[PDB]
Length: 261
Length: 281
Ligand SMILES: NC(=O)c1ccc[n+]([C@@H]2O[C@H](COP(=O)([O-])OP(=O)(O)OC[C@H]3O[C@@H](n4cnc5c(N)ncnc54)[C@H](OP(=O)(O)O)[C@@H]3O)[C@@H](O)[C@H]2O)c1
Ligand SMILES: NC(=O)c1ccc[n+]([C@@H]2O[C@H](COP(=O)([O-])OP(=O)(O)OC[C@H]3O[C@@H](n4cnc5c(N)ncnc54)[C@H](OP(=O)(O)O)[C@@H]3O)[C@@H](O)[C@H]2O)c1
Image (tube, protein in one colour):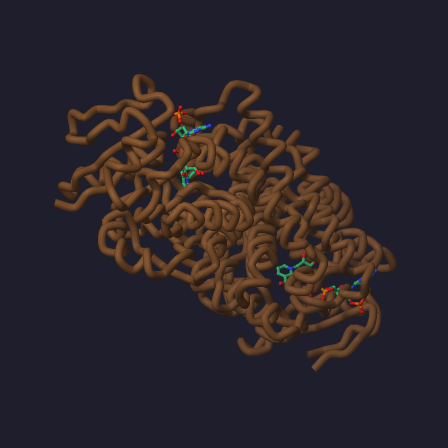
């Protein structure tokens, strides 16, 4: 038996999957619309069986407030994306009354092979139907740090996609352009493997920051001419400028790592 | 047996020049500074003393410099000796720089084509080397044979600046990727090491790279139907708050945030991240 809170795109995908493996799923929402046992209140859903999955951790505190009374005995798995510190404040608040997972998966991928979920009380932890489990510490907010990090790299990628598509829209359609992007991103995703190595040791040895700078300026000039915003690339430019100024004129794009603090 | 004449001996024009030698060509070479950027005729190259001597060295001319300004500057040389030649400018630049050059050089009897080298120097000659070419397709067809030694040719229009548009676009998406890598690494370094972290990033980016295929489709038709911009916004705010707490800069993500804020405000609260395409324009 499990009892879910939050029936958005992700909490439903999760709830649906627990059903397909024949579980006793209890479910709750602010605004109900289910397909399961429906918890009329948060108290009735707390006493049902606990996989929370909401908009923020504020919503976690807000919703579970009323149910101060029956927390004693339960094992709260918060899948809600958030900060490490939010997660630690919640873990201490809830352990005072008797974990965390970053779902590295879109809803459609839940139950799929490529689904993955990243911390907290390892007694309670010791889910697998949903995705490939990956525990990594008794630190209640370690999963959240790894969530946000991975998302940071995602959001880099989408920022490039959007800029790249936008910049070419006039001349060709986006799909016919994926014929060139998708391989190229593949190449460039490889080059980041041979950059984490540099970052881990401290090489940064030369495709030089001086020429890339005059390159990035050609994208900005070209973006304005195509009526596209180059605001996706500005931080990259600001960081390469810190680098050549600080002496890395002839060093690799790895060198910027020390200028992002 | 087949003769080429290069201009510009930086990291890229040397890689190119070196490769033409390894396929036993009659490679002529030129630079601003020869005594600087090596003119090792040792591997067989012929040093053009002036731009004129390098223009007359061959009828295939592969330029590759810092900017197009350097292209115009160097070839100025009252370019009367240009009639008959096939100028391949691999110099990264704007579509409009490329069109201004193509008209300038076609006025002097030459036949211009332009190329975005989608390849670092070490990749030149390799399987994954790729070069986009646009410009006079008459000139490109004749010299497609020779150029093919360097990378996989990919022609796409008689528009002298189409290769440059595709160059800068692809680079824009590269720079997005590195911006995410650096931010993502940075944010995690002080809890776990960058290499052990590529074990999670590299697959995940693979997933997310697939999702961009089914997003170009949306962008091409006009769906944007829901993974919603309202929740991602409170997500992106958690990365900014988390970055400050780890003493890391969240400056890589700010434009994304500014764009999602334009989107939910303009009504796309429940739409997919595809919807943002119309808010970069
Ligand atoms: N979708 C993805 O691709 C994806 C992937 C990985 C992780 N995630 C994570 O999943 C979390 C939820 O996923 P989602 O995509 O399902 O977002 P979602 O559909 O918006 O989930 C939000 C849920 O929380 C409830 N809620 C919203 N505001 C509330 C409030 N003020 N008080 C109480 N309850 C509230 C909603 O129900 P009511 O509106 O009825 O209250 C809704 O069911 C996200 O924050 C994100 O961390 C999403
Ligand atoms: N390396 C890569 O990863 C890569 C990848 C794709 C495309 N590219 C492009 O290939 C081209 C060259 O790249 P690179 O890495 O060789 O650049 P680099 O490291 O700066 O090479 C500099 C080259 O530009 C010349 N130059 C500078 N100012 C000039 C002027 N006023 N007149 C004539 N020549 C001038 C230099 O001459 P000196 O010898 O006197 O400096 C030298 O030939 C650029 O357009 C670059 O954007 C490079």
